[PDB]
Amino acid sequence: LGLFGYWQTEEYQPPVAVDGKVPRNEFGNVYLFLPSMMPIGCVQLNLPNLHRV
DNA sequence: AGGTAGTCACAGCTGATTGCGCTGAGGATTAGACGTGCGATATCTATGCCA
Image 1 (spheres, helix red, strand yellow):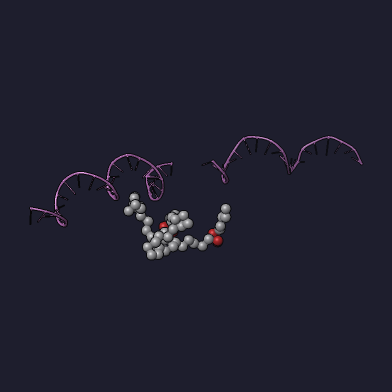
Image 2 (cartoon, rainbow, N blue to C red; image 1 turned 180 degrees about the vertical axis):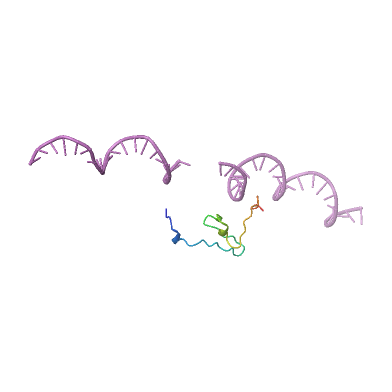
């Protein structure tokens, strides 16, 4: 397991939603450990059953 | 007076229907570090020996 140092890591730049498409990771989701990780043009909503709508 | 076309009333053909089965998205959920008792290893040095 490669433990990279602070000098080897710069910064995570969140993507930008294009043409009404939400960017997704390799697994089809978005990592939202921090608010800055949210892609530009995206909003997180805590609405139950929102995906069905 | 004579006859066959328009029309209405009972038969076949077919899609909708009520029993049942799959998918896809929700809400619930042990193997190193840190410290310790123990067992093997170091070490400073008081004292008696002869040349």
